[PDB]
Image 1: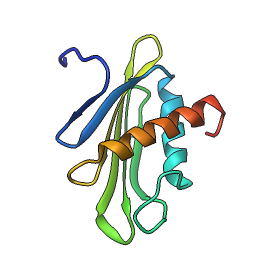
Image 2: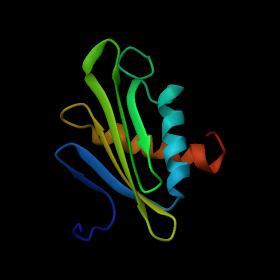
Image 3: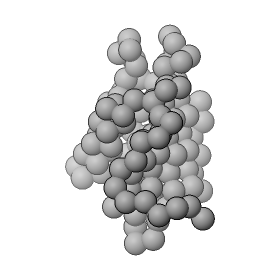
Length: 116
């Protein structure tokens, strides 16, 4: 349905990569990183989640800062075969490649060391 890609992508503010972890484990690890503030807004506060949904194949998380509605974090996830996960991260309206790469590392650490 979508063009073939390999490795990391960054376009129009969306940071996209593939994680070789189980789909539901990536979802839970990402919720954990947001809710407990492993990633945080400009004022050191956790982002406030307005919606998170998961049906086992597609999932999404939408969140934003309580003190700046433009300081937002949106995550989308898709299940791949062989326990792989395609993930898309966007910080703000313009994106932030560095913060997205950091969030990937936080998610991986949460899975590998059972902080979920």
